[PDB]
Image (tube, helix red, strand yellow):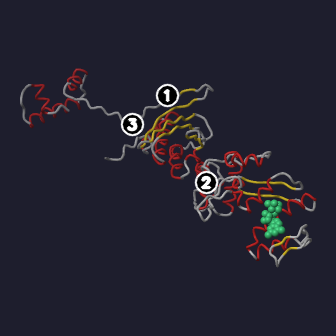
Amino acid sequence: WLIKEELEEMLVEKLSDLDYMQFIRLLEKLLTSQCGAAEEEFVQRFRRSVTLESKKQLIEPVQYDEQGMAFSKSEGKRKTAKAEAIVYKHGSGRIKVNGIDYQLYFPITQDREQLMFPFHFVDRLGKHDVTCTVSGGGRSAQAGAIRLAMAKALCSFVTEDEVEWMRQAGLLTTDPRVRER
Amino acid sequence: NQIKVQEKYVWNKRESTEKGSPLGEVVEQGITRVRNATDAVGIVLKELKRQSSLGMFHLLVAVDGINALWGRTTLKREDKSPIAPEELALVHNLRKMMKNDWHGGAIVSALSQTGSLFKPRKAYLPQELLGKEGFDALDPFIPILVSNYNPKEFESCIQYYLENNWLQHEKAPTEEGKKELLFLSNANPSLLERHCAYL
Ligand SMILES: Nc1nc2c(ncn2[C@@H]2O[C@H](COP(=O)(O)OP(=O)(O)O)[C@@H](O)[C@H]2O)c(=O)[nH]1
């Protein structure tokens, strides 16, 4: 709703709080009734705009490589680590990190679990191939960047309900926690 | 007792092994007096490499972590100087067995980065682990590749663990548990064994 001071600015007259409340209650009554187009625009004259745009993860386009295979590319960042992953529509579950198998690139089990989390959550372990390039940061930061990149790329091959579920599970959010000066 | 030496071996001015004695005596001389253990190993090798050529028996030379023989050591002198592998009698005598100058047997060996010295964790190929000297020594040889489990082997390994009741987690028998074990191990036998150990 239009605030009191900006309503004064539009009217070019000072007004109290109770009369502002009177006006707002009349506007509410007009809204509740079957207000027509003229009444709708009249209300919109006194209704300011605030944009809400959550729920909507930008789904990367599905590209096709020279071999005719469908894939999607995405980026992720965690601390100073930056990852860029290519997820293929079909595959056998092979992840390749900087050209190295994922179990050789990530000796620690925690990082392998982090890489597993996205595909496991949407019940498609062993159905996609991943080729990712990660740079900077350390062990866990690189694992988190790769996880974010794979989730954002995998959003292309899942249903919109599954995309929303991944969003709610925290799998599509860039983690902003970084070292404070 | 069947194998018998073909030379006189002198351990000390008092003690010697006379020609024609059973090889066991030599072995015993190394197990009782450790001072002559290393000399007793070489003699054994020198006998086994020779008599097999004569055709008395077939000899299998099985050496695990064979990449150690042509690399570096972490042993030092009293002046803290490095020691080379060829300066060890135990390592010097075992290199002769790797040379294909005898018949009547086979030489089977396995590389291993685990326990190796001055090799990066991801080095597994023959030249990378052996070095130039090691490859030149073993050349010509037949390399045999060992890979991760294929699906049949992985399924049978988990079935063996289930039959021994070694997977106690209630979700391990299920298909989703098997997929998670497969992803986390990537069908690697050692990783799968270590993961299954504490489940
Ligand atoms: N104490 C002692 N050791 C021996 C004797 N003969 C062989 N050996 C040991 O067994 C190994 C035989 O290796 P060999 O073929 O003779 O090579 P080489 O001695 O360097 O010429 C030697 O390294 C010795 O350690 C011996 O007559 N007395």
- Of badges 2 and 1, the one in the foreground is 1
Q: What residue type is labelled 2?
A: Thr
Residue behind label 1 places its C-beta within 8 angstroms of ligand 1:
no
Graded by Cα atoms within 10 Å as few (under 14), some (14 to 19) or many (20 or more), the crowding at tag 1 reads few
Q: Is any part of residue A109 visible from this angle?
A: yes
Q: Is residue A25 above or below residue B65?
A: above
Quick check: A179 left or right of B114? left
Q: Tell which subunit mark 3 falls on.
A: A
Check disc 1 and report the residue beneath it: A61
Percent position of residue A120, x then y: 53, 46
Q: What secondary structure is marked by label 1?
A: loop
Between the residue at mark 3 and the residue at mark 2, the CA separation in whole angstroms equals: 34 Å
Measured Cα–Cα span from mark 1 to mark 3: 18 Å
Identified by mark 1, the residue type is Pro
Horizontal placement of B132 versus A153: left or right?
right
Quick one: SS at disc 3? loop
Question: Left of A66 or right of it: where is A145?
Answer: left
Disc 1: host chain = A
Residue occupied by mark 2: B174
Q: Mark 3 points at which residue?
A: A55
Residue B45 visible from this viewpoint: no
